[PDB]
Image (tube, coloured by chain):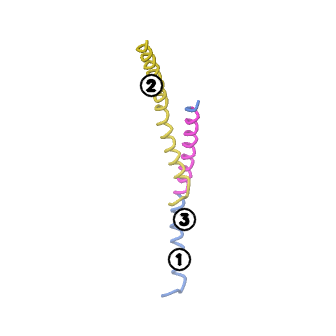
Chain colours: A yellow, B blue
Amino acid sequence: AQQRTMSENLRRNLAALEAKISEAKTKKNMLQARAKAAKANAELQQTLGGLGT
Amino acid sequence: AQQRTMSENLRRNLAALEAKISEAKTKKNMLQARAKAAKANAELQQTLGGLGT
């Protein structure tokens, strides 16, 4: 019975791990694009502002 | 939806950048001619004035 219990616990932990995996999969595709959009906005602001030369 | 939003933002920033590009294009052609007209006026004044020799 306790063997079955440990098996159930490990199954649930596996499910949680896979859920976090899916989270990271969903975050990766768009965070990089947003990072690049931020750099483009920074370039635009640098070209617009008169800060420095 | 947020992906679309970022796309719209980047499009508008592109438009702004191109507008500033057109501004510089319009300024360049005539600022140099005015710079040379100023030098010619300076030469005329130097030949006219009795400052120095």
Measure how far apart labels 1 and 2 are at the Cα level: 83 Å
Q: Name the chain letter of the residue that bears numbered label 2.
A: A
Q: Which residues are magenta?
A: B4-28
* Residue B1 location (% of width, % of height): 59, 29
Q: Name the chain letter of the residue that bears numbered label 1.
A: B
Badge 2 marks a residue whose secondary structure is: helix
Label of residue A17 in the image: 2
**Which residue bears the numbered disc 1?**
B44
What residue sits 57% from the left and 32% below the top? Answer: B4
Same chain letter for marks 1 and 2: no
Q: Is residue A38 magenta?
A: no
In this rendering, the label closer to the viewer, 3 or 1: 3
Same chain letter for marks 2 and 3: no
Q: Is residue B23 magenta?
A: yes
Left of A14 or right of it: where is B31?
right
Q: Residues within 10 Å of mark 2 (few under 14, many from 20)?
A: few
Q: Label 2 amino acid?
A: Leu
In which image quadrant can residue A3 be found?
top left
Q: Name the chain letter of the residue that bears numbered label 3.
A: B
**Which residue bears the numbered disc 3?**
B34
* Residue B13 location (% of width, % of height): 56, 43
